[PDB]
Image (cartoon, coloured by chain):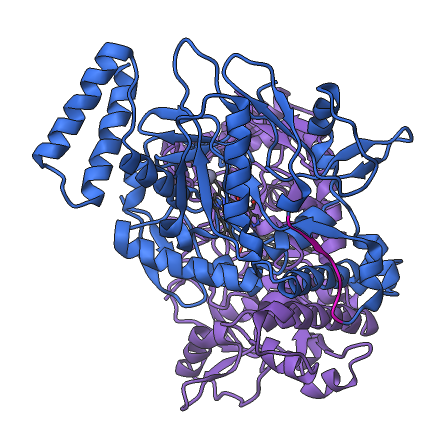
Chain colours: A purple, B blue
Amino acid sequence: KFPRVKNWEVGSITYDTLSAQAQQDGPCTPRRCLGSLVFPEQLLSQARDFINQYYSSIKRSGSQAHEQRLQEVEAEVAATGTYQLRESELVFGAKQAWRNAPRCVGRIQWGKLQVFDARDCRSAQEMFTYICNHIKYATNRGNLRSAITVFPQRCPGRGDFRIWNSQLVRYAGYRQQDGSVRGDPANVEITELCIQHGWTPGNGRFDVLPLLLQAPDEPPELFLLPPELVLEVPLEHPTLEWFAALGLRWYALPAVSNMLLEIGGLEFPAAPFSGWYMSTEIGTRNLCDPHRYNILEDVAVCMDLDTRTTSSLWKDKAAVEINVAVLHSYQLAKVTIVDHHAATASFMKHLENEQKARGGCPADWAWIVPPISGSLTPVFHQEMVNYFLSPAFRYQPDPW
Amino acid sequence: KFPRVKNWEVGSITYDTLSAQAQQDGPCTPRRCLGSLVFPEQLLSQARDFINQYYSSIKRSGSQAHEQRLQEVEAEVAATGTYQLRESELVFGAKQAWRNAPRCVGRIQWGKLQVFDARDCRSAQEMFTYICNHIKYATNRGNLRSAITVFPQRCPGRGDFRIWNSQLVRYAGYRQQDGSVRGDPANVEITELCIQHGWTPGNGRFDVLPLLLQAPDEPPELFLLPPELVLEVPLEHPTLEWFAALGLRWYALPAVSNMLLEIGGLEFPAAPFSGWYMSTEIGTRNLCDPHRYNILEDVAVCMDLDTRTTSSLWKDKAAVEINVAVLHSYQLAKVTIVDHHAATASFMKHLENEQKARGGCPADWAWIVPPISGSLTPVFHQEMVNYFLSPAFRYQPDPW
Ligand code: HEM
Ligand code: HEM
Ligand SMILES: O=[N+]([O-])c1ccc2[nH]ncc2c1
Ligand SMILES: O=[N+]([O-])c1ccc2[nH]ncc2c1
Ligand SMILES: [Zn+2]
């Protein structure tokens, strides 16, 4: 009854006993697999399970304190339809959410997460202050530290706190008259929203977007991150001298801000989190995706490669050097970064740790395997089981 | 409801309506996805469906001929417990089996498959002759032609025709006394079986294995493939002059021979098929997999790369040149080969053709996306739906 999981490189076998405890249902059915696709009593049920997880984590399950807590949660929901998490439970829940994220390859670090409690936040201005403090702590002058800031939970009588931006730091995307885009094409919508809301735009390829912050039942407010808080890295190549002349750069801090944090049935629509970059996301996805900066052809031409035929593998060669540049540049500027080989190796260790700890680990193979050199990394040869566990980070509709 | 399928590079959307016709069930459930895992009345229902597919294909569904055929099959099953396919149906069925294979990126050529009827095969010796003929026809001195040879179907009260080898052409794998393996580690088991049956083993890294052919209720017979029949390609690099000295080589013809062909409830345990190679399978998987030839480090050392740290991307760089070597060598030897960029590009066209033809296309994302430079290809950005349609090629247990 338990899924057999095999590693085809070494031949080792394991059984996922944790999958049987999946709290929610995925998109797949026996008739067809949809794994490649990107996207009252129910509250109490999830609440009780979470409390059980918490007390089990501190080795006090079945204790008087455990039973008391279960009764309090039940009492609060009966009277208000919701409940208040204790500080220690929020911290525990935030870590479990990261731990449970199937698409995250950096989970070996799940236990080291700084949790900022912003549940007392009352306005967009205070939300901005909290965000700036998160960025400063997380950036730590280049020695990045994982962190999450949790804003007030969704509740019955009012709207939600929301960060409109997809990440705390993103580059603007300006649609040009000729039909092209200057900057990040992925950010055209949010850029136009900022402009619509009062922001006079810049005209560069790497303009840091302002934050569009939303307090309950109020229109979003624009806030500009002090440049001194946004650490960036100029891109250069160790041997290709002309690379530095391209004027490319990227930001140090990858901070997702559009996901919803779910803990024991409670929902936190605004809870930005951050870690550090795995080089392929910048070097391969952000810079080489055809619908992103799309610099592959230009770099190849500068490398004097034959772009006439696909068989010369000019695309592969250019992509590799761009990734080399990203890694070399971050190391030079002393900003935390991890290559795909080192990251996937650490994930294999994580799988081992979790097998012993909980008898399995929800993992999304398509997202775990890096965008380049897939089969050269250990995770490629590792079968995985994908399932939804709670606490969890979930996608949610854009506020507009 | 029909699954909504999106391409994230372009933004186009389609609905897979074909998946509702999935005759068999997969390993996934709403509880968990297992997409990354490698592995009388019922006969009539499958037979009728297939016959219906056949008459629909020639635009004569509902005809007297269609009805007479359905009745003919029913009568044959009532009298013998099984039935026989007409030659035209066999051809159609084999082509559909390829068309329906979710893990095959080369399906745009499905309609051009050349099907050879070997159902009159009486012995292992006749089987060998059929196999040699297939090899000569398919290899065609380098100008490869897709083809399949179908041997007698499985029937009650009689053993099965089986080809013990996984492919018609495989390199021996010799386990050395010191624990290492000389040759292809993937072929250790079959090599030892060939030795046990009377084969005099060689001692090279690229020794073409003999065929272990099984006739109904007979022990497997050993057969040596005439060397002039096995076209091979010596590997060299266009700029790295020392690459040729490594003495690497690979065969021209990729001919899978251990899969079972299922058509309308009938099973053909022996039905070897072949096409032509996509470069990454040789350059990345066969030569660079840790559990295969594992030549990555040796090549990186010869390239004078810093193998001390992972961040220099020495593995990625070596892997790219190995793939360049494969492509260059096959093109030089004038043997059909397709790079991963051209292959994935053609698959996107195949998906387009299929959407219009059948309203969908069963595809396994994890297998369609190449082992290197995934995101650099269009298929990476394409959501897919995986399901089992029949006719089909299925895995089957080893005869031993
Ligand atoms: C510490 C370093 C970390 C590394 C190297 C890492 C790396 C990654 C990578 C490679 C992905 C896929 C990114 C993409 O394709 O967009 C990812 C996804 C994800 N990560 Fe991690 N991560 C780290 C920290 C964190 C932290 C601190 C959290 C949460 C507290 C987290 C939560 C997630 C989630 C929820 C996803 C899925 C995002 C989605 O579905 O779009 N990660 N991470
Ligand atoms: C014409 C050129 C062809 C190309 C470039 C091609 C390419 C591929 C590739 C890259 C794979 C997956 C990787 C692997 O082999 O392990 C594959 C799998 C497969 N191909 Fe194709 N193929 C071709 C022709 C054919 C033909 C003629 C048939 C059958 C009539 C076929 C049947 C299959 C099947 C059933 C699989 C799944 C194999 C498995 O599960 O291990 N292919 N092919
Ligand atoms: O999702 N994330 O927060 C996240 C964290 C770290 C990362 N490195 N590279 C991509 C990436 C994404
Ligand atoms: O399935 N096949 O016969 C087949 C055909 C062509 C191929 N290229 N690379 C792998 C591969 C497999
Ligand atoms: Zn699935």
Tell me if I can see residue B92 in this picture: yes
Q: Is residue B37 above or below residue A120?
A: above
- Kindly report the secondary structure that dominates the magenta region of the rendered protein: loop
Looking at the image, residue A392 sits to the left or right of residue A29; the answer is right
Provide residue B342's location: percent of width, then percent of height.
Answer: 52, 64
Provide residue A118's location: percent of width, then percent of height.
Answer: 58, 57
Quadrant of the frame with the C terminus of chain A: bottom left
Residue A202 falls within the magenta-colored stretch: no
Provide residue A158's location: percent of width, then percent of height.
Answer: 37, 56
Q: Is residue A297 above or below residue A256?
A: below
Provide residue A138's location: percent of width, then percent of height.
Answer: 71, 63
Q: Nearer the viewer, residue A231 or A43?
A: A231
Residue B236 falls within the magenta-colored stretch: yes
Q: Quadrant of residue B72?
A: top left
Q: Nearer the viewer, residue A53 or B239?
A: B239
- Span highlighted in magenta in the image: B231-238
Q: Residue sitting at 72 percent across and 46 percent down?
A: B289
Q: Is residue A292 above or below residue B4?
A: below
Q: Residue furthest right?
A: B178
